[PDB]
Image (cartoon, rainbow, N blue to C red; front, side):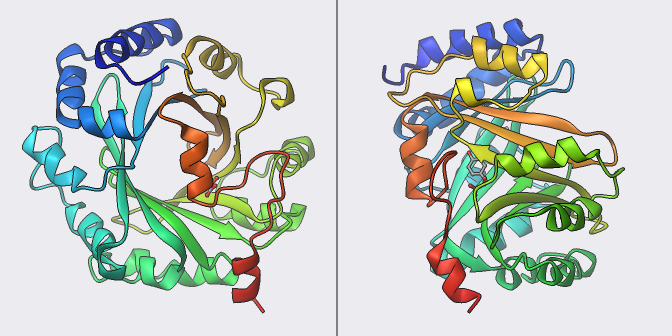
Length: 307
Ligand SMILES: *[C@@](O)(Cc1ccc(O)cc1)C(=O)O
């Protein structure tokens, strides 16, 4: 029911083996020792994608507010000279230090991402014109504003790939054309109509889309559309690897929480999935004002900012 650390170690080993993902035993023990409290007090959850052999990820969504980046550096999980540290510092220090850091880790490779919840609907300009970002990335602000992607709720630094994932909420409903315009940012081949129609059927009215930017070129590598807390009997068509993941990864939460993401990019499309483990993922998502599958997905503050 509750978070226990020895059980977590075993569930990491077991789940990685179940989906055919790599394992790094000592590195995983270091993450757990460095961030025990973070996992225990937050929502701890699982992630992977439909790419064959992909990593099993485990994360904490934070209730405890602290400098998780400094902790990761302390523990030898992140290089003290990582060139993206400046950006994560800039983002953490906005709005007088209100943003809260969470963390993603890979069972095979250690620290993967630092994720910031900014504590409201933030102007995209604030996020995208901190001086720590290069000109080439700041220049994409206008592409985003042109598509009406004007408010940001989260941003993640991907330490492994030197890129950033920016999470926007758009005023919808999302239609074929707006899908196409967002998808076109990614450079990848337009998909067939049933792909689009299925994605649209899972979106709330005011939709969540993640855009992945390379922090050195400003290239948009990837876009991802998300459906949160989809019940098992309402799931869209999924890759057998994702179906297996949702079956084998253990969830102890009172309310089960599965997340489905459709990722499109030039290197290949895939499906992302998240699944609750402990510490009440749904209750943290509700706190962030996320919209769940089969609900009212209307954002009134967003709608007042657009009128
Ligand atoms: C988006 O769907 C982003 C998102 C994705 C996964 C989790 O777990 C939380 C949020 C949104 O709701 O803002």
